[PDB]
Image: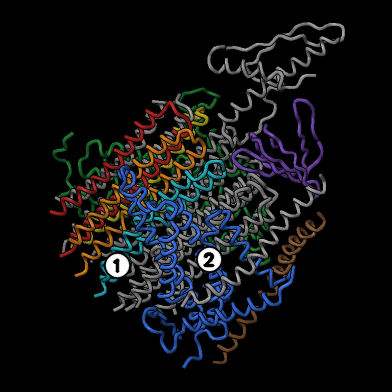
Chain colours: A brown, C purple, D blue, E green, H yellow, L red, N orange, P cyan
Amino acid sequence: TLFIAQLINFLLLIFILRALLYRPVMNLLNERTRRIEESVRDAEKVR
Amino acid sequence: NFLLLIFILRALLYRPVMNLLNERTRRIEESVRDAEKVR
Amino acid sequence: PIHLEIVTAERVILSDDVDMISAPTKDGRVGILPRHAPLMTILEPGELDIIKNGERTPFAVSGGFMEVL
Amino acid sequence: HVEVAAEVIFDGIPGFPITNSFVVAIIIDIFVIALAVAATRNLQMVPRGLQNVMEFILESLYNLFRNINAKYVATAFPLVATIFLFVLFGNWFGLLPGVGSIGVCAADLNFTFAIAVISFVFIEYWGFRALGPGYLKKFFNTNGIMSFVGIIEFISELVKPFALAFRLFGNIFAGEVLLVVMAFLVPLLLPLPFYGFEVFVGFIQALIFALLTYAFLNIAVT
Amino acid sequence: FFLYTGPPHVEVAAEVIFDGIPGFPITNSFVVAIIIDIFVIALAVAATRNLQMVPRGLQNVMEFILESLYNLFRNINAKYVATAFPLVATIFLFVLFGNWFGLLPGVGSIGVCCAAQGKKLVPLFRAPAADLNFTFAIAVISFVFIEYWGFRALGPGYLKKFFNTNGIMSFVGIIEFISELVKPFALAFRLFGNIFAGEVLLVVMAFLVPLLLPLPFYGFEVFVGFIQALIFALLTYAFLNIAVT
Amino acid sequence: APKLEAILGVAISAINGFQSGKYDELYIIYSEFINTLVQRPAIKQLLPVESPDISTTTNVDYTYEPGEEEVLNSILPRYVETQIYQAVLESIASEHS
Amino acid sequence: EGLNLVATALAVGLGAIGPGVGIGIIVSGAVQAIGRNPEIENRVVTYMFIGIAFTEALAIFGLVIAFLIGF
Amino acid sequence: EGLNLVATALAVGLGAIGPGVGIGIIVSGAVQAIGRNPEIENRVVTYMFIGIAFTEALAIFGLVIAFLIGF
Amino acid sequence: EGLNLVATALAVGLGAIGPGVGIGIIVSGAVQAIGRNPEIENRVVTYMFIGIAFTEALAIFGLVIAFLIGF
Amino acid sequence: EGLNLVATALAVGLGAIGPGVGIGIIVSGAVQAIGRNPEIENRVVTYMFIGIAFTEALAIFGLVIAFLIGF
Amino acid sequence: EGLNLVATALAVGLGAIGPGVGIGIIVSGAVQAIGRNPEIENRVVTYMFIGIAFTEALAIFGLVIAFLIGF
Amino acid sequence: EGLNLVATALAVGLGAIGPGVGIGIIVSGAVQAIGRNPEIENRVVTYMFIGIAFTEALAIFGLVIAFLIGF
Amino acid sequence: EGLNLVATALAVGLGAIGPGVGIGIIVSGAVQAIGRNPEIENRVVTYMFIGIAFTEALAIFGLVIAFLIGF
Amino acid sequence: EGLNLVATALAVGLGAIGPGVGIGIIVSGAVQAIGRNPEIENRVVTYMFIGIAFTEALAIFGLVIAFLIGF
Amino acid sequence: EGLNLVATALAVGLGAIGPGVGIGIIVSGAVQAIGRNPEIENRVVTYMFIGIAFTEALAIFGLVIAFLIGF
Amino acid sequence: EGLNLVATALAVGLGAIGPGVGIGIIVSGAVQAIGRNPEIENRVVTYMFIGIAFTEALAIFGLVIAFLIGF
């Protein structure tokens, strides 16, 4: 049905809306974690 | 049928295991190298 | 904005203003604030922190008491 | 109009021509392999995203297991890793990922039972391997007066993997039923983020299953 | 000890009617209410007495009771401790009087014509507490007094307590107003159930083994009646203060 | 300029003897620093009678998360110990004067 | 038919289980707070009575529904 | 039939449960306040007495209506 | 048939049991808080009212449904 | 069809449910108090026994009502 | 077969049972917290309202079933 | 017929429900109190025996009621 | 018949009490923790949301059947 | 008919929840008792198993009677 | 008839209150512990998720039989 | 006849609850004791698992009896 198709399309839109709120937060979290690993690697190089 | 990707993912898991161990080992080498430099 | 006064038998440690306290109370860590409710509690060998506009100093109180009003 | 149906099949019997559960498992495996290929060949010293998944999932789970049980997390690392990176992925693929059991000309009981059988085989193999007679300990021994239910405790442990399989099939199937109900009445999930709640519930269920496996292993340790 | 006899039967009813209906419709509850009011007036007259600061003399008891009630009302609040004090004192010793007289000899059998016929032997006691009309009237009067006090003190406050409690989104009103409205009906039903339940117990339980079974039952009933009178008196002031607050 | 640890060696012994019933009352005599010209002895008690510093001027009910018994057991030894410390330090000042 | 009697019994039983533990923990908390301080005991004693009264009102609703069913 | 007897059983049992559990918390709070500040012994006696008096007030409501069903 | 009477009994009872213990917990916690520190009674009492009203909302929902089934 | 049997069973069970959950909390509070301080001693014992007898009375009601149906 | 009336009665009562004591316990915790930390209202009362919103929302879903009986 | 069978089941179940949580609270309070301090072990053990006796009294009352209904 | 509507009412009632009191306990524990110390509020709120999600899962389990029976 | 199965269901279900949570109360109480003082752990060990045995003695009364129903 | 439908309602609905309160209590204790001691945050989380694994397993014991009896 | 189905639903309905509240309460005491004393470990955990097993034994009995009557 047309209404069902709109709901299915809207489900993807909600996922994208959720991604916009949370995915950038996760990316920043990974960058902080990766930077910490890089900082440890930098410490090894400096040591 | 469920274990089809178990062993396959084990190689992928084993591949990143060394990288994590290497990153962990860098901290050990960082402490040893830093301590030797100070001494 | 509460008058914190860390005192000791040998001398007084500090008497400055404070925004937050991280009190290591015996049965469980408790926070103190500008207009805190009345409390009076024993401390244990542990770690006490105070926040100065977002700066943490580890006083590391080894035991004692505290009275909150 | 509600049209939900049970996808119960026999793992022992040959796969059916439709094989909805098998198809979902294949799709999940393909997606996981695609992610692994994207993160392996295009891997750098400090990758972002590609290595972020590894660092925040595999390393985090290894650290958690070591904290819970160090030197035994290493031994059963493959079991917990297999529990992870799966089931949750199958549910994400089954969370109305463009199909929603529509346009056809974990929830499977057999798969959950097989997973619990693998968990119980992990018990029979590793747990009490350091003792051998550990399974007989505190079970009708000389102190059986205070340990009469010890054999009952073992039966509960035997029933613990079965309950884990039930919890894998349950909730996951529930999410499907709730999505079908929302489609039948009040479509597009619901006023609340039904889809998001279902996804979070599936992820929490997968994490809880992995933690339950690790905790059962630790309990078998002592 | 044994209770060989005396357990004739048991019979209860919602209420009891009285005579005098020709000149004006009178129920047995009205007769009981008039008797309680007369007893209260007589106690006040005796309590007043010479009123020359006479200590003890059975007037000091009434003075102490009034002082305790005044202290309780003052502790509850002080905005209307003086003006509303007579209103609460009206319930005090009147609900108490209604609770009393239920343990009188043949309180449930007073005015029965006679188990032989019972044609028109309506029991003309019908304890005023044990009547829905009296409790409903008292609760309506109390609710009206509370509403009037709230309107007089803060007319905007009474309306703003519900309509403007939280204008944005939802508000405490409606639910709060509905709760207050149920509060009058709740108070009425409280007096209706109380006293009536005590009488039903004194009938039924004493119908079987009326020897030391009715004694603790009546003691508990008297304590419950006094507690209920005090509770209603304090609850009127509490609702008034909540309206003011 | 002694530390409180120095007086602990006697304070804990005295309080242990007190709790065990070996001693029933505790007193302290010290050279009170009345003035730089006069230093007379002064007797004080170490069985807290009503803490007459400011009587009960302050009236705020406190919560005893350890508990009343635990609070009193922990604080009273500390109070007598600081009283002993104050007496000893006053006596040192009197000695030097 | 006798099912009205069952209705009344169920109503009063529900209205009795409801506020039982209610008033129990009410007066428990009241005596607790009184023990913590007998100074403000009067204020808390005043405040707990409306709580008792609301529970009693619910019980009375349960009882008078049974009586209404009876008549 | 015995459906009225079932009604009496339900009324008495489900009206005994409430006060029965409640008074336990009542006197438990009472003895706790005895163990902490027993200075209030008179107050706790009075307050626990009135609290129970409410509890068996509910109980006797249940019992008397149960007898009425049995009547 | 008597199904209406048992319906009203079930409605009022099952809707009143909850708010009974609810009021119990409400004013219990309120009285411990006030005895602990009654300087903030102004708000503690306000919170109790808002909370008392919230539970009484469910209580009166049960009561009004019982009344509607009764008529 | 044997309605009195289920009536007696329900009466006994729903009369006996209460006193256990009561007495639990009852003696738990008193024993915690006496562990804190043994001074109250008999005084608390007396406070406890009468409170337990109060629920014993409801147990007696539960047994007796079933006995009446049972004979 | 008037099972709709008992159905809606049971639905409203036995859906309102839970959120009642839920409101009770949340406001007990909140009044304790305010008796500890008053100015934190801006955050703690926000969490209060969130937990409140879940509870009466569930009860309101029960009420929607009660109205579905009307449908 | 079967009514006696379900009657016995209800009797035993509703006679076991109460004493279960009863003895649970009994032992929890007792172990907590004896953990507070030794030297009152004999007295807490005596109170423990009193508690288990009082709970198992109602337990056996339900059990013997079911046993007698068995014949 | 109407028994299907009774089934839905019972299902929603038993599925609403559980999470209804659950979320109340969730937020209660969270708010005592906050009032104890408003410094770990981030972790406290995260675990509170996890508990809320689990309770919502239970509610959905008890709620979807209400519409399934309609099917 | 299946009323014997209803009897077994009631026997296994009712009378199990009571001891089921009583066990939890027992062990939790013992746990905080030993956590506050581990030197009394031997006495805690002695008390635990006996309390667990008594609650399980109630549970096994619930179970073996159901087996008797099964015959 | 619809007795299988109301049986499905019983199966799914029952076994929800207890696990709901368990989901409450597990995180209540966990957050109390973590606020009392944040250094144990990992271990408290693990001991929280084990309790999750048991209580959700009970809830799914209810749900799986609800689907089995449903089909 | 679906009465056997109703019996099975009711059986498992209360069968998977005993541990529900039990794991809820047991974990609370465990984590609270750990926070009070993090030094003690593995003894609280052994008692923890013993209590979990004893609690869930009743649930297993309920489920297995349900299966036996259902097949």
Percent x, y of residue P63: 33, 63
Up the image or down, F82 lies above or below P65; here it is above
Mark 2, residues whose alpha carbon is within 10 Å: few (<14), some, or many (≥20)?
some
According to the picture, the residue beneath numbered tag 1 turns out to be P67
Q: Residue furthest bottom?
A: D105
Residue type at mark 2: give it.
Answer: Pro
Q: Nearer the viewer, residue E145 or C12?
A: C12
Left/right of residue D62 with respect to residue E221 in the rendered view = right
Q: Position of residue E82 (x, y in %)?
A: 61, 40
**Chain containing mark 1:** P
Is residue E207 left or right of E72 when viewed as pictured?
left
Q: Is the residue marked by circle 1 packed among few (<14), some (14-19), or many (20+) residues within 10 Å? A: some
Which secondary structure, mark 2? helix
Instruction: Say which element carries label 1.
Output: helix
Q: Quadrant of residue P21?
A: bottom left
Residue E225 visible here: no
Q: Position of residue H70 (x, y in %)?
A: 22, 54
Any part of residue D111 in sight:
yes
Chain of residue at mark 2? D
Rendered-image quadrant of the N terminus of chain F: top right
**Residue type at the position of mark 1:** Phe
Residue at the spot 69% in from the left edge and 29% down from the top edge: F58
Residue E225: horizontal and vertical position, in percent?
40, 42
- Where residue E1 sits, quadrant-wise, is top left
Q: Which residue is mark 2?
A: D78
State the residue at coordinates (62%, 83%). A10
How many numbered marks, from 0 up? 2
